[PDB]
Structure formats: structure tokens, C-alpha cells
Amino acid sequence: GGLLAVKHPWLSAAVRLADRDGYVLSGRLSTVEHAWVLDHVVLGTVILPGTAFVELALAAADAVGLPSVSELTIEAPLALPARGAVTLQVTVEALDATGRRGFAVHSRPDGAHDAPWTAHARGVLGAAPAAATTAWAAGAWPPAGAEPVDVTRWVEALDAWVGPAFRGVTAAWRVGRSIYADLALPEGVSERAQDFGLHPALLDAALQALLRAELGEGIPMPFAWSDVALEARGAAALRARVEVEDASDGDQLAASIELADAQGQPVARAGTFRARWAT
């Protein structure tokens, strides 16, 4: 024994270091078992979506007893092999005075114990506001004055090469600064949605909602996250409120995401997520 058990599709083991105040989490991401991940294709290459690093961080967070991610930045995409697996590792660092720990997410081609590790994401685990109220999701759906948004169109930025698991927006509307949306996964991927804290395809769908609103040149590309917390795990379809921040969206897009189930109760919140426009 001597290993802490983590209940997650992509993480299986955790050790507390005796050398340092820290933890090392380990796992495997097999393309054969999560085939849906292959639907996330970016310019010809299957890329692990950024929301998957959010889920990995959220899982490490609960494992070391610090729920929520304070900050998360993706500095390198993780390309996945069709028909294969990747080894993952989360390094968690010391506790600071704020009551938070830094962390990093690494990957290594599976079976290659010789191969070097690759850093993909860094951030801070810690105490964040866990949205206990989603006032907007209760009551009339969509909210009063909601103007429907065309999700059904094909935008190169979103639908090129992509398989059905990442076409997860049923409906969307905009009211002032807010985008509201119905998010749902396809019937096949919905199966294991209970197995994730928040299904990465489900959380990506909230980003598709905002991208199809702000493309209705350059593509806003998400790379960073703040104050992300999970209230209810295993959600398969939810209502979303995406509120864009006013601060001259043009060089860099920033928005808030909150998520609620069909019954109006809170599921998750991301205080802000950052995207930067680029070709």
C-alpha cells in the first residue's frame, strides 16, 4: 500500500512527499476508453481540450483537501494519439499563507518510461468562492428579454475537424452582457459524465456558447482560468450563464461562467476565464 487512492478516470494514485510539503498525483489518459476526446481536433491534430486541465486540477484539488482552483494557465497543448494513451502527473507544492498550493500538470507518452515529461499547465489550488447561488437559472428559462443566438451555423473556428462530442450547445440567447445557453452532451458521451466532476466536453460547451456569440480575422483562444469551483459533480446537461467583461474586449476576451442544472441549482462556477485573439 502506502498510496492515497483517488477516484478519477485520469488519476489513480497520490503520494504525500516525505522530503517536502507536497503531493504527486499520477494517472493515465487512454484514448481507447475515452474515445470522445478524439472529437476535439484543432487544425488536424487531436488536442486535449483546456477544460480537461481544469478537470484534472479540480480532481487534484479535492484529493489534497483543497477544493477549487484559484488560477490555471495552459502553456502547452497536449497532443493525443488516436489508439493509445498518455501518462499524467500532477505536482502539488507547499501551502502558503493565503491557504493555497501551486501545482503543475505534466504528461508523458505512455509505455515510454525513458521519455521526458512535458509541462502543460500551472496554477494555484486554493480556497475560491464556490457559487452557492445561481439565481438566474431558477424562474423563466430563458430569462426575460432573451434574444436567441444562432448556434446552428458552421463557424470554421468551432466546427472544423471537430466531432460531435464538442458540439454541445443545444440553445443560446443573449441578454445585455450575459449569454445564456442550454448545454448537453451527445447520448454516447453522456454515459461517463457521472464519472467526471465536470465533464470537460460539458464545460467546453459553455465556451462554444460564448464563441458562437462573439463570432456573429482572429479567433479568441482560451488559455487561462481563475476562481473555478465545483458545487455538484457528475452533471450531464446544465444551463449556463456566460457574462462577458466590458474591459474593451478586443485584444483579450474575459468572461465569467456559471453553471446550473435543469432544476436551477448550482453546479460549477469559473470566476473568470481568459482568451486572447489570434489567427
Image (cartoon, helix red, strand yellow):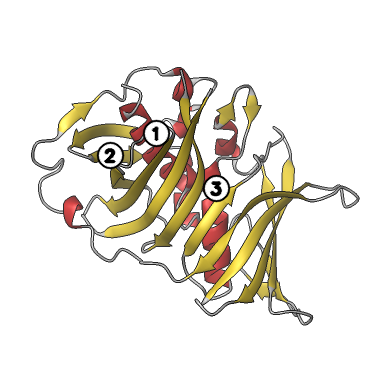
Q: Return the x and y of residue 233 as percentages of the image width and height.
A: 41, 60
> Which quadrant does the N terminus fall into?
bottom right
Judge by depth and name the residue closer to the eye, 190 or 89. Answer: 89
Q: Are marks 2 and 3 in contact (CB under 8 Å)?
A: no
Label 2, label 3: how many angstroms apart (C-alpha)?
20 Å
Q: Residue at x 42, y 30 (%)?
A: 167
Please report whichever mark, 1 or 3, sits nearer to the chain's N-terminal start.
3
Q: Nearer the viewer, mark 2 or mark 1?
A: 1
Sort mark 2 into few (<14), some (14-19) or many (20+) by Cα contacts within 10 Å.
many
Q: Amino acid at mark 3?
A: Ala
Label 2, label 1: how many angstroms apart (C-alpha)?
11 Å
Please report whichever mark, 2 or 1, sits nearer to the chain's N-terminal start.
2
**Side (left or right) of 80 relative to 189:** right
Q: Residue at x 40, y 61 (%)?
A: 230
Q: Amino acid at mark 1?
A: Gln
**Direction right: furthest residue:** 114
Residue under numbered circle 2: 182
Residue under numbered circle 1: 208
Give the structural element (helix, strand or loop) at label 1: helix
Q: Amino acid at mark 2?
A: Asp
The number of numbered badges drawn on the structure is: 3
Judge by depth and name the residue closer to the eye, 104 or 141. Answer: 104
Residue under numbered circle 3: 52
Judge by depth and name the residue closer to the eye, 250 or 274. Answer: 250
Label 1, label 3: how many angstroms apart (C-alpha)?
15 Å
